[PDB]
Image 1 (cartoon, one colour):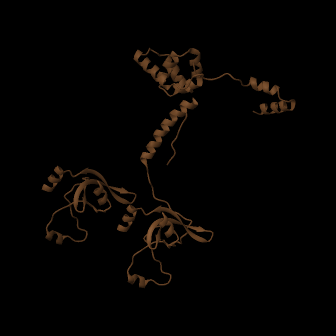
Image 2: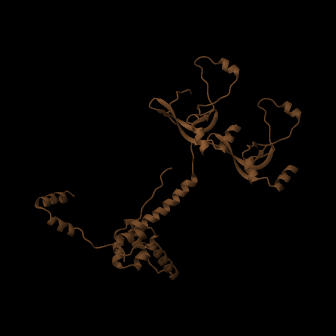
Image 3: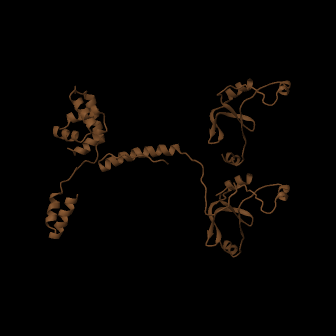
Length: 51
Length: 110
Length: 87
Length: 87
C-alpha cells in the first residue's frame, strides 16, 4: 500500500453520474437536429456520446 | 415548387400512408422524382398504398396541410441556375494547351 | 490604505503543511528509524497554507526547475474554516 | 432566517434504526452466540430516521457503490407521530 510521493501525479474522483445533464443533452440534441435540418435543408443524425 | 431530394427526405420521416397521400396530392412528375429517390421497401409500400387509396377526411387533410406548412423552412428563392459542367468546359477551353492536356488527364482519372 | 502600505514594509512568514495526524506517545516511542507514519489527508488534496500558524489558503505542490512550489487553488472562507475547525 | 443560518453552522447527528422489540432480561440471558432475535417491523417497511434520538422521517435502504444509504420516503407529521407513539 505504501508508495513514494510524486508532485507530478494525481488521482481520480470515483463516479459523478449526472442524469439531469444527460437529459439536457438529449433535449439539446433534439433541438439542434431540428435546427440543422432547417439550416442545411438536409436531415442530420445527432448521436449523444457518453459523458 | 421544391427540389425532389429535399421533399423526399422531408416526407420520408412520415407514416407511409401519409407519404402516399401527399404524393397523390403532389404533381405527377414531382412525385415520380421523389419516389425514385426512396428506398426499395418504402417505394414498394407507397406503390401498394397508392393502389388502394380510398380518400381522406377533410379534417385530416387540413391537419396534414398545417403540419406541412409548419415543417417548411426558408425555401424562398430555392435553388439557383448559375453554371456547372458547361461552365467548366468553357473554362477548360480558355486554359492553355498544356493545361487542357492536364485536364484530359484528371477527367479520365475521376 | 496608507497603513496597508506601512505594514507592507513589514515582512511576514508563510508556512505550508503537508498534513496532520493524531497518535499516542506510546506509539511514538514504538516508532524507530525507517518507521512509516500515515496522515489524515489523502492523495491529491490541496495542502494548507499558514501565515504565522494561521491557515489562509490552500494550494497544490509543484516543482520549479529544482525547487518545490505551491500553486494556490482555493481560500479558507469563514464557512469552510468553521467547518474544518469543528472537526 | 439569520438564526437558521447560524444554527446551520452547527452540525447535528442523524440516526437510522432498523427496528425495535421488547423482551425480558431472562430471555436475553438465554440468548447466546448465533442466537436469532426478531423485530416488530416487517420486511420492506420504511426505517425510522432519528436526529439526536428524535424521529423526523422515514426512508428505504439502498447501497451506494459499497456504502449503505437511506432513500427518504415519508415524514412523521404530527398525526402519524402521535399514532405511532400511542402504540
